Each structure stands twice: as structure tokens, then as C-alpha cells.
Length: 376
Image (cartoon, rainbow, N blue to C red; front, side, top):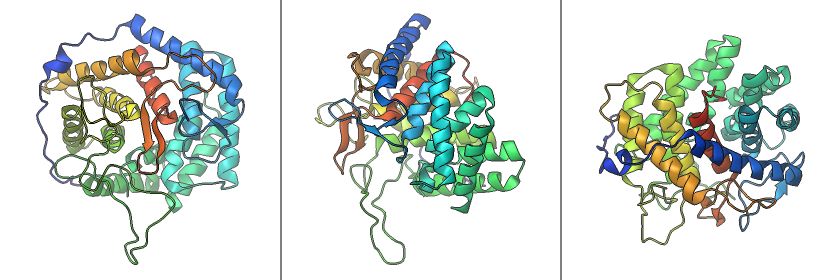
């Protein structure tokens, strides 16, 4: 049941967060409005189909339901629906849900590492919203695919299993989720609180698995989104497990992230880079970290000396995303959020908008604006 000890860095120069102005209702409302305008334009662009994982020169291409990222588009639609209650959004998003149920029924392009990312923001999302029985059906079937069956993004993936346990009462879902949390935490985070990131080779033959490549600059580096998967995945798991160790681990990983932010508090694509590097940012990592911090602060004791710093830090990061990184060109195919990095080593979506970045940015806005019931 034990999490390995990690170094928890103190938060350096906390006044760089504490002196920020908190985001106001009007500020978040207008950021939501601007995102939704692009979303409604993109509804006529994508139709019943989906954006590609990332943009190309800041314009998405249109694809079918065969990637790891399709759920994030549906997630954007549901989040928009949380805001304006527009049944148009419900209609289109539910059609995505039916396409996801078809996808799980026929086992079309399914990798078990992606199931949480695919089915939570789409199907579990609708179940949270209106209790749709086909949405539940798709989610449980995805959970079962995950059960038949280590990277840090498994901390997000296992949320599907906790949901399955809650809906079925079957302790086996919870058993695997809990085991997988500790397996990931003890193996995928370094003792300095940075996420481990490696080119993965077969443990028995030494063969690489292509055509995918490594994430993060190098074996010694700190991939920003991997760091964020931890920052968000830990509190999500904490909801369901309530191991105080998880809070300490969050503090380690979050403080590490915060200490490596540049002047505008938006992470470079790898945390070994800062101002002057000439490297691209990954806004998607920063959006994800805001969500994770926001989630953890629901539970973090008032007596934690850094709770206020975390509050101001997430406001600081989100403000920067809104003011400097959100999309201002309302053209078909544009993303909600600019300057992400998908896969640096592959040259995929480098300094481009991406769909998970868009989703987590909108999720952060919705989190700030209302009392949001989690899809996760």
C-alpha cells in the first residue's frame, strides 16, 4: 500500500503566483464564450466525424473514430453543454456516443492504454449528465476491455475502472485500479518527483515497438504532459482511495512542475527548457495541471501552508492560457488553444493546437465557472 519516498521541493518564489489577480466571473465567462464560438464553427466543419489529434498550421483535419483522441472532441461538446444547456450539443455528442458504442462492440482500433481517454469524456460524460443507458453500456464494455488487458497516463485510464466498480459493485474493478495506481506511482515517477520517460523496449528480446517513438526530450528529461498526467491523475485517484500518501506525491509532482515554469507560467514541452531555449511550449500540459490542482484543492486541508499558493498558481496559469494562448481567429478548423506539442520526436503536432489541450483548457474554465460534476 506504500508509495516510494519522493523529494518534495518547496515552491520557489511563490509570490510570482500569490501576487496574480484571481480570475473573475466575467473573465472566465468571456473565455468560455470565445471557445464556444470556435466550437460551433467546428460543428459544421467536423459534422459527425472528428478532429485529428493535432492541428496542421493551426487547422484540424477531419477523421473517423479510430484514434486515441476522439473522446476529447465529444468532451468539448459536453463541457459546452454544461455551460449553455443547448440540446444541439447534446444531440451531436450523443451521436458520438453511439459511434463509441459501435467502436467498442466491433473492437475497432482499440489499444487498452487509450480506453479511459476515449470513453470517459464521451460516454461516461453523458451518463453523468443525463444517465443515458447506451452511454453506460459503452463505458462498462470499455472497462471490461481494460480488465482483460506501465505509463503515467494510466493514472487517468484507471478512472474508468473506478467508475465501473461504482456502477456494478464488483470489487475486481477496484482491485485492478488500486493495484495499477501503486504500480504506476512507484515505477513511473522518479525519486525527485519528475515523471520517468523512456523509449520502451521488449523486456525479453529488446525489440522496440514501432511506429511510435519516445515521449520527452531524453531519458534524463522531464516531459511536461507526463508531469501533468501525474498532477491530474493523482487527485483523481485520491478521490477513490483516500491514501494521504497520494497528497504528498501530488505536492512533489506539482511543486516540481511549478518550479520549472517560465516567466508567463506556461510550461515548455519538456521541463528542462525555459525562457531563451527557443523550444516550443506545450499548453496542453499546463491546461491539464490546472485541472489537477483544481481537483486536489477540493480535498487539501486548509492547514496546508501551500494551499493558497496552489490556488493562486492555477489562477496564474489559467489566466496566462486565456490571455496569451487561447485562439482569436474564428475560422473553421481552428483549435481552442494554440502552441501545444503532440510528439516532438516524431515531428507530429509540434507547436500546434491539439484536442486534449482544447478539452483540458475548456475543462479548467468550466471547473472555475461552475460546480462541475466530474466525467472522470
